[PDB]
Length: 21
Length: 21
Length: 21
Image (tube, rainbow over all chains, first blue to last red):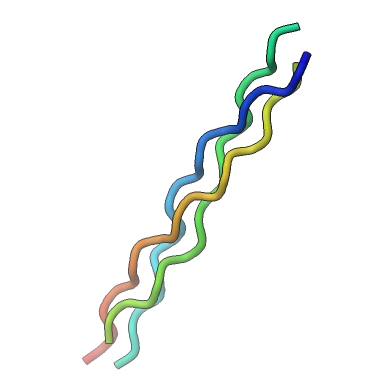
């Protein structure tokens, strides 16, 4: 048969890095 | 035949931005 | 049929922690 529909989106990425001083 | 299953879940997004100074 | 395409990447991650004093 034909392929299914796309999977769902992933979750958010990792937290960003600490800010500078 | 019927459609296949939905695709697998997507992966994570990119890392977030830096924190505030 | 076969599985659908993988889902898309998630959105950007959250901001990082505040920087040091």
